[PDB]
Length: 552
Figure 1 (cartoon, rainbow, N blue to C red):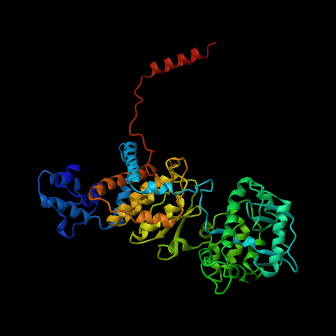
Figure 2: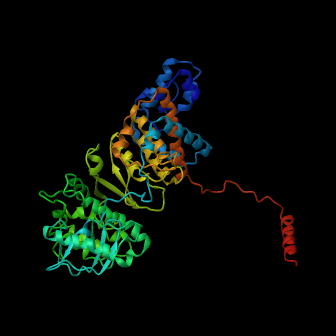
Figure 3: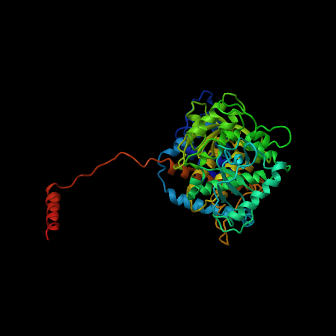
């Protein structure tokens, strides 16, 4: 193919089209209902290789750009481009897989280097120390901060525990008849007693060596202490309980509406919208009162995700008055992940997930509806065929797919989903490669890009393979500012015409190999057999050998 491009000096923008269509024209169906496609003997689309060699030494300067323009017009129906590209990648691509992946994996080093990514990565300290897994948004610990109040005064504690700044408070939740804001005026004097309580009972916090100074408190039930002694149960729970108080520490400030919005959706009018959403008489069959009483009264199990509060079943109740029955059913049966319960509740796969954080920065709307996919935790094989303007998304361990059109819209969604889940891994843990590059592949084939968006994805292959490399000090940098992230990705210098061809050749070949290994078929039928050996000269020889072996 290369002499066809180098002879006519076909530029790199056209050569992106011909490098795709050589793999597609072996199966590119066509019905020549308008007769423009035929090239003097045959379909030039369906026979793209033979017509290319025929147009090579014929030496026709018009017909070179004629065949590429006939190839670009072939590619416009991008939907069935994806059906033929992916199906052509599922059979064994019988070539040297590793050495092609090795050199193209070596070219993504220098592209990272000559980009400003390596200069930016030195500034990205405050490293990815052992909390590398990013927090979930459906799962929240905001109900446990409320004051447990009975008839007259706050319940005296039974057991006392502690984390780094937050204080734990164990009480039997059969007692407290109501729950009330810790920012209350009459309790504000009482509240600073109980901070002085805990550092007198339990000084420097048990889970880490940190000398004692308490500033917040959370009130917890009693049956949780039997689980919070267990070790891995603490690590998930503590950083999810301490996430609540930093939401709580902005409540008097002008930021707070964003935390109320992304966690809930609808916002109350009036002062304290956070508390006067979380604490209101809501529709129930059993105990017609606030939703913290719907959680605190109901127990948990060994799974740590059952104690915290699920938002997805909540936002059903906020918009339909049936759904409040379904909120109390989940808290009894105590399932772990949330989206699976809907699929087994005989429910349509559509539900809502909100992204107020990035949508205020760039995005169109934080609100969207998704199509769920199955609860997969072990298999990094995404194992799901995609069609009709869709894209992988992940919240929790459930994958989901989103209808998204006009792939500049679905460009940015990929830059966000990479920003969540590719962190912590790199050249060593390959679990971020084969899923991440598969996302980078689909956008590059299912949708149409412009010139500058080819400069965007080369930054992402340099980001997935090399963003979390251990730096010159051995420190592994942390990409956390989305305002520093997307402006580094989306805005940059425009690529050269010739380096477009060199980069897209490195993109498309790394795309094809990751699809090939995760979707090969190494099980086959035996295409041959050779039991052509002699009968007795094998058997009486092998029977002698055993008779010697048994002899002592």
